[PDB]
Length: 258
Ligand SMILES: [Zn+2]
Image 1 (cartoon, helix red, strand yellow):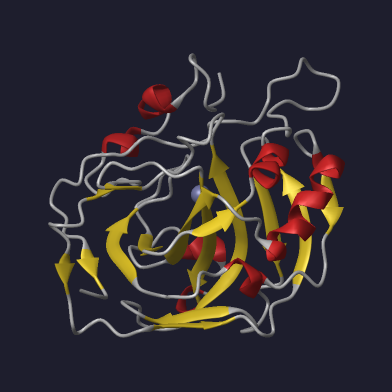
Image 2 (image 1 turned 120 degrees about the vertical axis):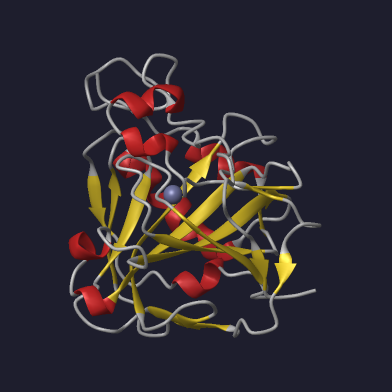
């Protein structure tokens, strides 16, 4: 039936409806730190989120998205391995049922408790829908979350989850500053990949930050209280909405640091 993360519709079944799942530039991957090539020609990332305008938070049945106004160049990513300007459209997370799993990318096979994805689209394409059809249409910043100390800047998010518990619910979510979600260092790994959920288009330049941010156990617990199901349907907790690492195939992972 429709795709999800259960036994009968999970990642291992996606290829039936989305043949691109067994493609040549599928994401996530395992980051082998000894095989990643330091590339001194890569520029530092430029994150200009001071004018970010968030609008809403939504439970789409597979995660929760915080959406931003992308009608102008207010929150953009540029530099790094990118050419042009990429506008932030939304951010979301992938998490697990336990603290030992949840991230999509792994580092030397280490899994983190969750992974944040900031999704950006290449402004030369005019809109998000056109951008997904191009090899350089999107740039996704990925940030790992480890459990330790609470992240103050994440609390506003945590607090509104009760109101979007089931699929299709949404809530006004204005004046949220995504700068509160960044690690101190912007060192990163980069590779050409895809979206990690259907339709799995190979249109992403991945930018994975080396430094994880910490969240408290209690903050992550609140994530695990969301539901995959819609209101009045049997309860299925929203946990383990992560795709396992895919084959690197013909790709090189580059590092911005040594
Ligand atoms: Zn994602």
